[PDB]
Length: 332
Ligand SMILES: C[S@](=O)c1ccc(-c2nc(-c3ccc(F)cc3)c(-c3ccncc3)[nH]2)cc1
Image (spheres, rainbow, N blue to C red):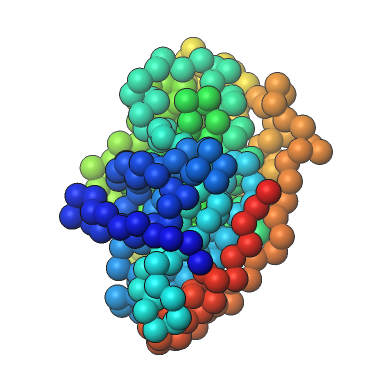
């Protein structure tokens, strides 16, 4: 058990091992710091109010559980996990530690003008991660350009993968729809890609209903085929109210962009989550011909998420977590 300094950063206080030095605020709370033990730069995240509510406490175990599982180049994982306390009784803090990344993808579309080859590498990467994630039966639900960490290199990893702007949500999340599927991430990836290629937000909706309008001026109103599946004597309904729309040509909507890419968008941005192309499929798409390599798009171990499915007490969750903290084996 390592020696910990203590120091205060802004209002938040910080209690970490000496192997990390230079703690430096990037944004619970994140600091950039130097890992003497490996001499690589890292991100230390101090979880906010870990075991406040049951809703926090479970959320804590979830985050630790996921991060412990994520072993994949395109997906944030755990270098170190640590608590200052010793024995169960003191335990009320959790700092998570990963490879520092230092820019997110929203400060890229706001810097650069990006090449087609850029979106290529970048989107491939997103789908590389996605696909490992989906293979564990986890669904992101919030992919958006601020959950994608990119380092100076143009390397990218997926942040917050399975913890949870309306702009990147599949329509089926904006219609609640309590029980959908993994292709919701695909919709987002479309929204991200479109914007990477064009420099403007695809669907900058002002609220939840404006957004289903914006989506519709593009992908068009649903065929009686899809309409039937909307669970409503009237939640339905509510769509057909709003005028009937031409499905626009992605080709013009997206003039100038590589037509491989545009064909790819036509398949991600499909109103019907059954006809939405999967992660593993979209990587076999020509757009990624440069990068693709079947024998290098790895799946994940199966992920145990029955825990999700049950009501424990604060005391029961903080205990399980602590089990997770001390049971932690670091990588290579
Ligand atoms: C969705 S909100 O925009 C949001 C922003 C940042 C983060 C966010 N969480 C982390 C973070 C840090 C350490 C971990 F172990 C896990 C995640 C980072 C991070 C990781 C590596 N290098 C720089 C920053 N960014 C999570 C949510």
